[PDB]
Image (spheres, rainbow, N blue to C red):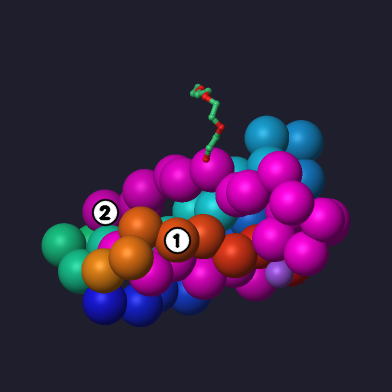
């Protein structure tokens, strides 16, 4: 169950619209390769594994 969203740099968060059409925010990791490095970069959310990867 995979989603693409957009991340924000200040809050280091991923915003994705879930299957119900509801916008949901979830934290990006602190790790270098998974943090949001720029506003409006892509991010992915795997709700099966509950894993977030921001760019
Ligand atoms: C606001 C939530 O704070 C949780 C702090 O716990 C530290 C654990 O590190 C994060 C592991 O994914
Ligand atoms: Na990334």
Question: Residue 51: x, y in percent?
Answer: 45, 61
Quadrant (top left/top right/bottom left/bottom right) for the C terminus: bottom right
Give the residue displayed 20% in from the left and 69% down from the top. 19
52 in magenta: no
Give the residue displayed 76% in from the left and 36% down from the top. 10
Q: Which residue is mark 2?
A: 22
Question: Residue 7: x, y in percent?
Answer: 64, 56
| Whether residue 14 is situated above or below residue 10 in the rendered picture | below
| Whether residue 18 is situated above or below residue 42 in the rendered picture | above
30 in magenta: yes
Quadrant for residue 39, please give it: bottom right
Cα gap from disc 1 to disc 2, whole angstroms: 19 Å
Answer with mark 1 or mark 2, whichever residue precedes in sequence.
2
Comparing 4 with 29, the one in front is 29
- The answer to whether the beta carbon of the residue marked 2 is less than 8 Å from any atom of ligand 1 is no
Comparing 48 with 13, the one in front is 48
Question: Which range of residues does the magenta coloring cover?
Answer: 22-47
Quadrant for residue 30, please give it: top right
Any part of residue 32 in sight: yes
Q: Which residue is mark 1?
A: 51
| Helix, strand or loop at mark 2 | loop
Q: In the orientation shown, which residue stands out farthest toward the left?
A: 20
Quadrant (top left/top right/bottom left/bottom right) for the N terminus: bottom left
Q: Is residue 33 left or right of residue 24?
A: right
Question: Residue 49: x, y in percent?
Answer: 33, 65
| Helix, strand or loop at mark 1 | strand
Number of numbered tags placed on the structure image: 2
């Amino acid at each position: 169950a995979k989603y693409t969203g957009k991340c924000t740099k200040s809050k280091n968060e991923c915003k994705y619209k879930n299957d119900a059409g509801k916008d949901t925010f979830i934290k990006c990791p602190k790790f270098d390769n998974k943090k949001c490095t720029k506003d409006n970069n892509k991010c992915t959310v795997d709700t099966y594994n509950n894993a977030v990867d921001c760019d």
